[PDB]
Image: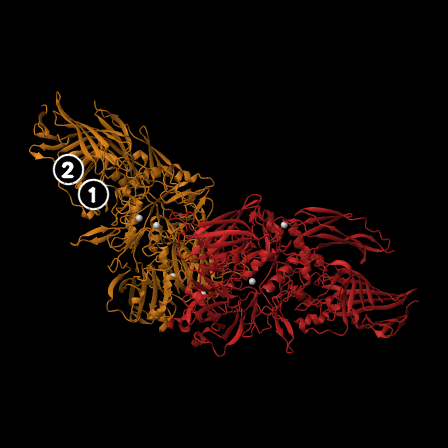
Chain colours: A red, B orange
Amino acid sequence: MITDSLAVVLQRRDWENPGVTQLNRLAAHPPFASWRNSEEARTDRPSQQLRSLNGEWRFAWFPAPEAVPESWLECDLPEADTVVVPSNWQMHGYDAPIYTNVTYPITVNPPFVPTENPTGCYSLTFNVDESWLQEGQTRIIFDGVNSAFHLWCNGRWVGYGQDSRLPSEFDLSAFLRAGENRLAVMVLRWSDGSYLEDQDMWRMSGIFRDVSLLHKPTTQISDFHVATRFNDDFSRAVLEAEVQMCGELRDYLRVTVSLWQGETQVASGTAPFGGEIIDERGGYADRVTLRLNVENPKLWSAEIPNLYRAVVELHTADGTLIEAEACDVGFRVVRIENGLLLLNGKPLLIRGVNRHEHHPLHGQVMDEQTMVQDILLMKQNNFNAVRCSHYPNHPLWYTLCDRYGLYVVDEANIETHGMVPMNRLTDDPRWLPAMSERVTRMVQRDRNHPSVIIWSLGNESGHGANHDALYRWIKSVDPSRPVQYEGGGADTTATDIICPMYARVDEDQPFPAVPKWSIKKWLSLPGETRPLILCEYAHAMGNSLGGFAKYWQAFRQYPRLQGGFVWDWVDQSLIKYDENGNPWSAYGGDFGDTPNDRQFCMNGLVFADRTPHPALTEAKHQQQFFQFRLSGQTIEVTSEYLFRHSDNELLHWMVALDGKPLASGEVPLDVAPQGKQLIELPELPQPESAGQLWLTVRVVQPNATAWSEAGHISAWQQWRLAENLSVAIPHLTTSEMDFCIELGNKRWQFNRQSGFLSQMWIGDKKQLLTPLRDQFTRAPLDNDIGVSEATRIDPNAWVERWKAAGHYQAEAALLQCTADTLADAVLITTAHAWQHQGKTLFISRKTYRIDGSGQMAITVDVVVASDTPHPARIGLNCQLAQVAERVNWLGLGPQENYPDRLTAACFDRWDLPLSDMYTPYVFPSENGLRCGTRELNYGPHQWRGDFQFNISRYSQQQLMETSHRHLLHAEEGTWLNIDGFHMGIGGDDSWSPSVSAEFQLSAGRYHYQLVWCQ
Amino acid sequence: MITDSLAVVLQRRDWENPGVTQLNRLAAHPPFASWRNSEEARTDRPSQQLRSLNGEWRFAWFPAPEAVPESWLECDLPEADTVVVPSNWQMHGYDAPIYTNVTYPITVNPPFVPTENPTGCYSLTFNVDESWLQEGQTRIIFDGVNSAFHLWCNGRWVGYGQDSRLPSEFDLSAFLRAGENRLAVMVLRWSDGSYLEDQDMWRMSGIFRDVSLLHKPTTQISDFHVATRFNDDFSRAVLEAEVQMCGELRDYLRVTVSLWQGETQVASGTAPFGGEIIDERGGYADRVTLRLNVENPKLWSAEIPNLYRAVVELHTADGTLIEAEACDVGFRVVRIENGLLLLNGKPLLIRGVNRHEHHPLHGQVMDEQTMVQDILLMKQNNFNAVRCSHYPNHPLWYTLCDRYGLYVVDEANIETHGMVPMNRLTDDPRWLPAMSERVTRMVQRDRNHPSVIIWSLGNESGHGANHDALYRWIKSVDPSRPVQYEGGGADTTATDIICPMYARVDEDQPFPAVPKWSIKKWLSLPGETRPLILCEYAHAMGNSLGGFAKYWQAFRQYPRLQGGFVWDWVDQSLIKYDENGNPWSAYGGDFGDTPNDRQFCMNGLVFADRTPHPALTEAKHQQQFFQFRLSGQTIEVTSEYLFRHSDNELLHWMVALDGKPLASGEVPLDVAPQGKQLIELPELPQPESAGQLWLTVRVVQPNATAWSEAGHISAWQQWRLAENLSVAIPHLTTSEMDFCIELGNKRWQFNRQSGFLSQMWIGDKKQLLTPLRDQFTRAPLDNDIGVSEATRIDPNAWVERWKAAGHYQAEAALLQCTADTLADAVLITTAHAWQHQGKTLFISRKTYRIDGSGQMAITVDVVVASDTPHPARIGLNCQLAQVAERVNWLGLGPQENYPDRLTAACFDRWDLPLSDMYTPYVFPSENGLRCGTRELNYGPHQWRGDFQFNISRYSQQQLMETSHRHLLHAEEGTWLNIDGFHMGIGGDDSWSPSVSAEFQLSAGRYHYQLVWCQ
Ligand SMILES: [Mg+2]
Ligand SMILES: [Mg+2]
Ligand SMILES: [Mg+2]
Ligand SMILES: [Mg+2]
Ligand code: NA
Ligand code: NA
Ligand code: NA
Ligand code: NA
């Protein structure tokens, strides 16, 4: 037909009109399956009325919707490939995914999008049974289509949809025919809706969530809401189920709502349709509210995710079932009382993380297995909350969070970050309809999920009146959940929770019109009474999460600081393939996407393959649910659980002397929620030998859980106990070029022109490929770089200050190199000055004392100019000629730890393969540091003292000059960096200096001593 | 083109889709004229860039949009008539206007409308100058089109619009061509928008407001808001003018905002574009806010409508004017403080009325002359506020209210009264977009008008979440005005003001879920702190406004009772024409409209021709701005003005004895706002003659005003002063049939079978056409009938109770008729029983004493059964044979007054033509009563006593059995009803019993005496 033709359908350009967000789309509603059997519904068995169209579809790509041929509406194109649906077509190579953070991927001219609008033409030929078309309603459900789409069925135009992150449903009953049918879906990458979808993520497109057919009866359940009300002590609950119907009303129709705990019916209710009178015209004849009483309900929480099963049966008075829907019900109350967010009467402490729907191979297509993997890892690392950054998630997500026990912030798909000002659209009433659909349809879909405890109005869209309106709309329709929104300063009228992004613990960031106060200060501002939960904090970009412990100290000290959501869970890297077929991880700009925000897509605690970064352990430790205090030999264990007794926890303790165990034991934990348990340690040993005693306690979960295996370690702490302080002569040969010291089969060679230990021999085997030289620089971290780019320098970034000061180009100048034979040792004294453009940045004065035992004692005293940027490190580095399989050390470990991220590390004797001493951050940087190290063993070498170290096959130079980890090549031998001092890594944010003063190397004078021996 | 064709344009049926409220419509904005001269703008002179297309258009009517021929898009139809635009096409006879109140005029199946959808095809061929199309933007403005419409220009489809009551603007620049152009407008009577337009009014359609062309420059003023901020005492003001631009930004662009008081520039400000930073992305580069200081501003109020002129000039830095817009600015603050609505720091007392846009000949087309007439009448009757029931009004309205001084409630065009429940749509998020457009676009249009002091979210649409959302939206965008909304119980979260409809003063109406408490009680409900202003009260349907004084006593006694809006200003009657070309007033059902709400369209204080009903005077008296208290000979005059001194008022006083003046005088009023003035009266006379002294004071405005002529009476009061109490024999001839009494040339004849005075002779001329008989009934008022209809009886209505009790059918039974000659008089004693179906309702026992002076003294004692409904009246009626030109009476007058509506009437000697004793209510009923009457003179007849009376050419029977006033025919002679007692008329509402107990004839025994003589 003429009006079904592309030429007509496309003429109005509905994808460039925010007044048209949909055409012929059905109302939003909770998940439906149209069970015709109540036991199936109760048991969540797969309904035959819900059919999946996921699988092999036909796909053709076009540069613009105009280029689509009319024949596509009737027959599959010859040029059409077979592709899997759901999928993003950028993952199939048709065009490039674009990583941009704030800047829109298109020209900013709303509501218009580029004429070159990549278009994906999907089609599916399928069979429909005669019974479906004989009676009832057959709808098609698109759980996600990015960004917009037109839908044809058998050549006839059905409808149009936007909002990539919520389901779009269309009635096909009048379009289907018994037997073979063809769907034709034209998906546009850009639409007016794209102005509300400016999230900091990969910009992709396609039918990336499930496609289904649902068959319902003519007389059907159209919507149903569950609410739970409680008494003062949660001993009595009322489940209020409001059920709505569509179709023909009849006095024999009945609704039965039954509530099940496993196989046990705990409550039930039956009633005819017809609600109570609500205004002068009457009530809803097509609605009914059942009120079921539940005595001593088992309450839902992230700690104990007790769930009931609500089955909603639409049937006849004589008992014939018309259809059945069902939901998981969690009995919990979420409310803000006197400035505190309470769940079931107790103040929450949100151990949260932001999570994008990202898969390195399938992009933004989510599968159950990846969701479960994420949830398990999160709970195993002491997360209890997740923020749907920044859009409604795949439906299954919420179910899993109901089942496994995670608190969820459900967020509308509204982000206009790229607008100038940020609220240009959100303050414009012409965009209120569009925004409304993104909020309302989210609530209507997800309001029955107990896991969802907070609604969010979106992200980074300023503060406009549309936010206030939709805030109030949510509050009116669902007063069971707080609403939050960070835009416009994080404390606007459109949020019940002060929810700033990257507000620091103690440091104010007074930005014009939207300051980021210190969270502590923020709570106390005149007139402010709300709780404060950071929607984003602790930016985990690369080697980061420095200063995380400061946040958690504050969270625990301040009642109204109820936590936050780390940014973020998983790196948004994508897999590309080398010429040799090898996969490597790619970030912004690696797909020809331009402009792009290069590696800012990788802010995760875990790699895209869900392998953890070191920072994750820090989080786990700071978020652990058991806090410990040592008093003498008494351990006070305090529980931060609100609801569960410690019924699956035992405390293992161990006392060790310089890594050697001396005593241990196990004590079952029996501590009530928010309670204390005192554990008296038996008299620990009094080792008369020298060294520091260390007490380490670990809470172990002996039995498996739904989310953890037996023996899971959930918490730990370490304290220093008592310390007992410790109470042949080398031959020197002097030449014009070097001092040579010989002792047995050991030989040291100091170059007199450079002033450095230039070679060491054991027997005849050289030990150094590069001299032992002072190092004051590190391969910059993403936090060091910030947003600085070779084209657009950011002068306040640490890397730019270091480069401008000449730290990387500083030329060592020999001031002194002298040798002297003592009674039993040889003493080499050196002094160097590092200079740049006439200024002396650093002066190092060293002494090397080589004694009759072969031990070389190195004393290093460094002066740092007060006016030069504080150096990243003060230490030594050399390239060792040997490559050994393993690294042994007495120090903090086992994982990478830095001065502002080492609380989770434990002091012990650690022994790891050399590879585990390199952290493969996709963007290479300084990595692998271990701090608090008293002994390091590598090959025949032993270093002793009190130092930090990293050891790898990659130089700091190579790390600094290589953009991707897959481009690194192991160099000859092994690079050893031994630092007396190392700067913090930061992480409060990764676009401004974030290293706190106490972790900057600002003392001006530094001293450290090493002992190097065989 | 194919896509411009009706077949394509109409295929999507945008008028049955609430997701499509418009296509290609431009943003809403304040009134624009695009002056290219700043003096013109200042002087509000007509801009040549604003051209009117009002005038002769071509029009063709069709029963459905499908029936429109494609040729219409290119050339005018042959069948097309020439019609005036603006117009409603029901007023041109093409189809019928439908009067329905609650029930939708279409089948209720949203969003769908009937397939038979009357369609009006308008077209206009006009000329466009070349300059308009050479550069700049040419838009077409439709200030009102009911209900929806598609727009073509020169055969090409431009756009689509809904919301009949706000302007719809479209850019024609790309469609126009130098010289001759043709607009084609297809207007649909029904659309999805019609579900939001269920106001209790005539349902009409067409282009009923102005159509204009506006030419603006490419670089233009796109929006501008004015705000006024004040200090604690309103001595200093800041005018904050936010100006927005569209087009190309350039650093030489400037905005100048100048403020004028007549010809005097009081303030000015210039600035480049670029607003302050508002969020992280910056500010609005295309906006600028000027902040002008005004010292000692002249404040705007309904009492003193001081206005400034704001001229907004968009120009270059070097001084070239690009364009100029302008507005009237009123400096006033509206805010609710501690439960009180304050204007400029003073609590308002709203003397309000609801006003529909209605004209009896042109329907819903409004002209300036009618608006001015209405405003003048309102102010002359002591109204200071108007509610735009129930939609945004013609723009000019607001301007006039700014100029003349009326407070305005601006109301969104949202009424869903016919839905079941009433909030079915307003609680549905799918209708939130549509509703939003009706609210937002109202605010954007009218927010600069000082007269608008309150926003309303609509009317009779229940309470749904959409209301809460839009309430909050208004509060966010314009916090300068309170928002009110009555739906959902009048005290919901969506209103700042308790704004009930027809809540009574002392009587509760406990309806389920939406009770109408007594307003006094309502204020004091636990937790209630808001002010209470009735959005509708005192239903002026016909002979009504009984009990109005109770409302105003309450308003004055209770601070938080700040008044209300009477329902309503003007009868919504329409003019039809008899076979003889005579015009008559018509109401529901007179156009074949069915179903219809017959006469409920006529609820006005004035007739459709703006002739006043009697009730208006009552309102004027109760709303008067001067209150009086008498103490001895001292009059305390209290001013209820808040802002103005009584600078144009003098008090005239007069003392009169039984209507004869004895003394008078004038005293200038000099009373401050809310102040008191004591006026000592000189020693009033001590007339030793008999009778009651009456003091009457009137406030006269000696000088003309913009709204009143010289000598205007604005207030009055009357008190009783001292009273000095007053300290030939007829021949009887008895026959079997009658007693005959003769005295000189006077003869009385009493029938002994009936027991009534059956004839009276003066000389040989009979005086009676009908005997003098007791009357206990009245032709029912609309308040007596309520909603009762012959098909659907309402048993609690007074008329139905009276009919069921037999009051109208009661048969008089003679119990006694006897005659007796006294010393100097003849005494006739009678006793009658009125009976129905065996029950005696009334018993009348009378004595007629005819003495030697010709005077017939009648004593009447009536017993009323306690269990029969209280009778409407207790009196006598006769048909007098004579017709005299005038009626003289000593009593309350001059206008119709009833026991619960007589405060405004004054006791005096009144003399009016007989016609003025009949009030021509379009729906006939009891009318013309004058109460407190001590003397009545008609022809040679004089009646004396203390009675109420009406006198007319129409019997109560005829009034009762005639549906329209034009169908009344004067009967032979004159019907006189003399009542000892008369029931109240009611009026709190006209669909339930509203006569308060103290005005019901419930005493069971009544006595009254008359003296009838020559
Ligand atoms: Mg659109
Ligand atoms: Mg962003
Ligand atoms: Mg529509
Ligand atoms: Mg109504
Ligand atoms: Na806290
Ligand atoms: Na990022
Ligand atoms: Na009052
Ligand atoms: Na009415």
Disc nearer the start of the sequence (2/1): 2
Chain at tag 2: B
**As drawn, which residue projects farthest toward the top?**
B823
- The residue under label 1 is which amino acid type? Leu
Q: In this orientation, does residue B712 appear?
A: no
**As drawn, which residue projects farthest toward the front?**
A318
Residue under the image location 56 percent in, 43 percent down: A232
Q: Is residue A116 left or right of residue A832?
A: left
Q: Are marks 2 and 1 on the same chain?
A: yes
Q: Is residue B462 left or right of residue B858?
A: right
| Quadrant in the picture for the C terminus of chain A | bottom right
- The residue under label 2 is which amino acid type? Gln
Percent x, y of residue B374:
29, 49
Percent x, y of residue B696:
27, 34
Query: Label 1: which residue?
Result: B959
Percent x, y of residue B256:
43, 59
Q: Which mark is residue A128?
A: none
Label 1: few (<14), some (14–19) or many (≥20) C-alpha neighbours in 10 Å: many
Vertical placement of residue A447 versus B544, above or below: below
| Quadrant in the picture for the N terminus of chain A | bottom left
Q: Which mark is residue B879?
A: 2
Q: Secondary structure at mark 2?
A: strand
Q: Quadrant of residue A581?
A: bottom right
Callout 2 touching callout 1 (CB < 8 Å): no
Q: In this orientation, does residue B750 appear?
A: yes
Q: Quadrant of residue A360?
A: bottom right
Taking depth in this image into account, of A585 and A945 the one nearest to the observer is: A585
Percent x, y of residue A537:
62, 58
Q: Secondary structure at mark 1?
A: helix
Label 2: few (<14), some (14–19) or many (≥20) C-alpha neighbours in 10 Å: many
| Count of residue discs | 2
